[PDB]
Amino acid sequence: KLQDSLDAGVGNLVDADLAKESAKLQSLQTKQQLGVQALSIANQSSSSILSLF
Amino acid sequence: KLQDSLDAGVGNLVDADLAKESAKLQSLQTKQQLGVQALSIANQSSSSILSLF
């Protein structure tokens, strides 16, 4: 019983809760897609100058 | 007879009624699957934002 209690304590110390990761992962993939699109929009700033000349 | 009465009283104090557990177990299994499906539906809320960009 003491061995099982020590294993349960190690699991309480280190084990991740994957159910939270199931949402946070998809949120981060949506966030990286939005960040890539925002960087693609920011990259275009130099093109506006060409119209002026 | 006294020892038999004492053992019957201990059984009245601590023993479970397993016939009720036989229904509660199946109901809780169905409820657990339904909760897993509902949480899986809840995880997907971020995906709708990608359609707007």
Image (cartoon, coloured by chain):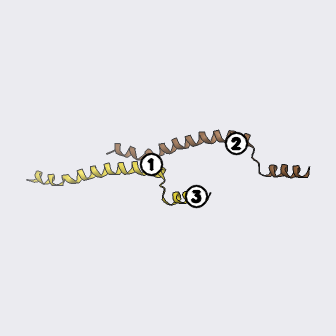
Chain colours: A yellow, B brown
Locate residue A20, reporting x and y percent.
47, 52
CB contact under 8 Å: marks 2 and 3: no
Callouts 3 and 1 in the same chain: yes
Residue beneath the point at 58% across and 56% down: A4
Callouts 2 and 3 in the same chain: no
In the foreground, B4 or A42 = B4
The answer to whether A10 is drawn above or below residue A19 in the figure is below
Q: Closer to the observer: label 2 or label 1?
A: 2
The local crowd at label 3, few if under 14, some if 14 to 19, many if 20 or more residues have their Cα within 10 Å, is few
In the rendered structure, the answer to whether residue A41 lies left or right of residue B3 reads left
Locate residue B46, reporting x and y percent.
40, 47
Q: Chain of mark 1?
A: A
Separation of disc 3 and disc 1 at Cα? 31 Å
Residue beneath the point at 30% across and 52% down: A35
Separation of disc 2 and disc 3 at Cα? 30 Å
| Label number found at residue A22 | 1
For marks 3 and 1, the one nearer the N-term is 3
Separation of disc 2 and disc 1 at Cα? 32 Å
Element under disc 2: helix
Residue beneath the point at 80% across and 49% down: B11
In the foreground, B47 or A26 = A26
Residue occupied by mark 2: B21
Element under disc 3: helix
Residue beneath the point at 75% across and 44% down: B17
CB contact under 8 Å: marks 2 and 1: no
Locate residue A28, reporting x and y percent.
37, 51
Query: Where's the N terminus of chain A, which quadrant?
Result: bottom right
